[PDB]
Image (cartoon, rainbow, N blue to C red; front, side):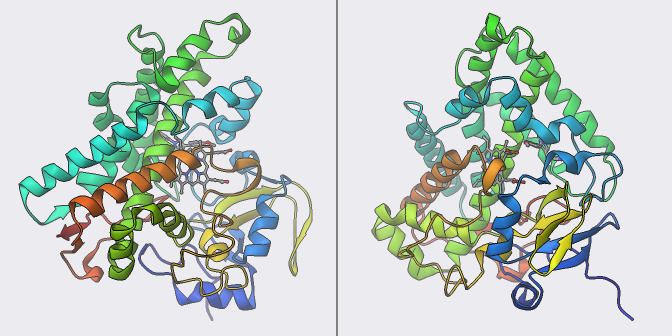
Amino acid sequence: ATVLLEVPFSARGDRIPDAVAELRTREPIRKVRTITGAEAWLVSSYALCTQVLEDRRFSMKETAAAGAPRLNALTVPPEVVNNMGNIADAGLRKAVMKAITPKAPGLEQFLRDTANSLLDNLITEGAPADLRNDFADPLATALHCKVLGIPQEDGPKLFRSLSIAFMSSADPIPAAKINWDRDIEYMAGILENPNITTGLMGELSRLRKDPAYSHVSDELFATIGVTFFGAGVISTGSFLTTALISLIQRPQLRNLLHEKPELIPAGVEELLRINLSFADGLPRLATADIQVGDVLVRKGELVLVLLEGANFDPEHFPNPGSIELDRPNPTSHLAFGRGQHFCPGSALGRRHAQIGIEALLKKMPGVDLAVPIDQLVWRTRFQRRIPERLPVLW
Ligand code: HEM
Ligand SMILES: COc1ccc(-c2nn(-c3ccccc3)cc2Cn2ccnc2)cc1
């Protein structure tokens, strides 16, 4: 006898398990057991993943309900699971989304300067260099301090919350509440700090004192800062890191993008499509009985939308494991989700990766792994898949 199939299948971010394609072909929605012991429906085809994400009766907010089957333990207060809904109800969605576009004058040049300085320091120190800890993550942290309007010198401490905040744990995490409360206190202080006049926090600070927002809570304002810093930094740092592995693995593509940087946006779009950064399916709780493929999902059941299921589906992306810069449907992947909860930072995440890669290829055109790929250490029980270190030479 065997036990019910357990998710996640693998913490490795450098290869997709053969099991994904087998499930997609034979059982594109099928029952699995999560790390908490709960049962869930794992959805692994493009067509069914899109159906789930585009039907709001598969609810994000209700995943936080007491007694629900859980993918993993909450690491934030349950109301924060509905963060974007709370932002919209407060009348803040347009202002938040304007503050986090990569369009602020000087932002791209800031990103370019920061990337180049980080790379110069690695060259001075000599190979091997760690492109996660000493390039991709600092670049993500610096970008998000700039976008939020907060001091660069505060970035490192805020960053150090993230290896716990973004755990994917079977049980509640005591350190997560310690760090959450401290970071909330920090952002609350930022809102009262007269030096903070730019970026997302500068704008929130002004709206907070505007009569049209006098009954929006100070807790929500601080929460926006904590959640956008954390989600943005973890997502961009982790995506860039694993994208760099996929690029290093492909010397022909590396050289092409070095020789024609105008193709970097199309290359980043394919790197997004093939990215394994999300460690778990996206969770949703059914609020009605809904037919998904051959399965009638019942009200109250947990559904997990496997992004690499959709993004490697050959019915939608032929030759799915190959980076092709000339696909006719290049942005139709689900790397940023789909529907009501589509990533509000998508443009910023694209630009972070594009500029980081452009700078790396100019400074280190011969970049290559400094260890055999099987020597990378894949973080476990985390909401992203990332190597603990990414050692390179050039
Ligand atoms: C390449 C980088 C990024 C990737 C791959 C990514 C991926 C995603 C995905 C897949 C979702 C949907 C989650 C779901 O539907 O359950 C999402 C949502 C979200 N992302 Fe991103 N993201 C990235 C960058 C960013 C940045 C830069 C920010 C903020 C500065 C950000 C903030 C958020 C937030 C707040 C949500 C929740 C949206 C909602 O619930 O409506 N992300 N992201
Ligand atoms: C729906 O927009 C969201 C945005 C962010 C989060 C989230 N922020 N942080 C976090 C960030 C910084 C410090 C500490 C915690 C962790 C999560 C993800 N998480 C945990 C439990 N359930 C979801 C959530 C929603």
